[PDB]
């Protein structure tokens, strides 16, 4: 079973903003997670072919990854911070739903999620 098309990172029909919260989401939140030692499995869409996960996209119908989020932030895809926060949460949720407690990938997601929560706890108020 092939990979699906990746999530959209460009859509000229979609209204966009550059906001201080979205800037924080790139400069602080994404940056922190991206540089982490456990970031690598999450830096691009799950390649179900290479990774021999033929049931992945049967189970996971809203795929998300930090490669996609990074592109969405750098290319100003979002209207608001909540959209981006939802993408991160979708990414973590997918990992927990597909895998089992104590799997390496789940421990990796937990570490990244801890940092995610720490950083969005201090999301600045809108300017
Ligand atoms: C590359 C790697 C590292 C530990 S397990 C694994 C392959 N499978 C993966 C990869 N990424 N993600 C997000 C998954 O949920 C699954 Cl199950």
Image: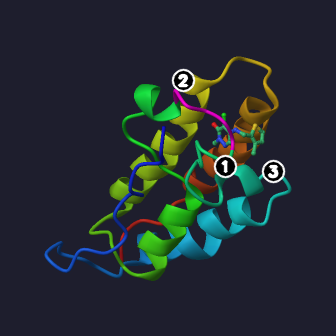
Q: Magenta residues?
A: 51-55
Residue visible at 71% across and 64% down in the picture: 34
Please state which of residues 122 and 110 is positioned toward the viewer in this rendering: 110
Residue 38: mark in rendering = 3
Q: Earlier in the sequence, mark 2 or mark 3?
A: 3
Position of the C terminus by quadrant: bottom left
User: Where ligand 1 lies, by quadrant?
Assistant: top right
- Give the left or right position of residue 43, taking residue 98 as reference: right
- Give the left or right position of residue 37, taking residue 30 as reference: right
Classify mark 1: residues with Cα within 10 Å, few (<14), some (14-19) or many (20+).
few
Magenta residues, dominant SS class:
loop
Q: Position of residue 99 (x, y in %)?
A: 64, 23
Q: Earlier in the sequence, mark 1 or mark 3?
A: 3
Q: Secondary structure at mark 2?
A: helix
The nearer-to-camera label among 1 and 3 is 3
Q: Position of residue 109 (x, y in %)?
A: 70, 39
Q: Secondary structure at mark 1?
A: helix
In the displayed structure, would residue 107 be above or below residue 102? below
Q: Is residue 66 magenta?
A: no
- Give the left or right position of residue 17, taking residue 36 as reference: left
Residue visible at 36% across and 70% down in the picture: 126
Disc 2 target residue = 97
Whole-Å distance between the Cαs marked 2 and 3? Answer: 19 Å
Classify mark 3: residues with Cα within 10 Å, few (<14), some (14-19) or many (20+).
some
Splitting the image into 4 quarters, where does residue 11 fall? bottom left
Q: Secondary structure at mark 3?
A: loop
Residue visible at 80% across and 20% down in the picture: 102
Whole-Å distance between the Cαs marked 1 and 3? Answer: 17 Å
Disc 1 target residue = 118
């Amino acid at each position: 079973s092939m990979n699906p098309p990746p999530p959209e990172t460009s859509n000229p029909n979609k209204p966009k903003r550059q906001t201080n919260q979205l800037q924080y989401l790139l400069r602080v939140v994404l940056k922190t997670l991206w540089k982490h030692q456990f970031a690598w499995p999450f830096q691009q869409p799950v390649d179900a072919v290479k990774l021999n996960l033929p049931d992945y996209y049967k189970i996971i119908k809203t795929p998300m990854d930090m490669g996609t989020i990074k592109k969405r932030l750098e290319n100003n895809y979002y209207w608001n911070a909540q959209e981006c926060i939802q993408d991160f949460n979708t990414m973590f949720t997918n990992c927990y739903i597909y895998n089992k407690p104590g799997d390496d990938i789940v421990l990796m997601a937990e570490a990244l999620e801890k940092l995610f929560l720490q950083k969005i706890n201090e999301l600045p108020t809108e300017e």
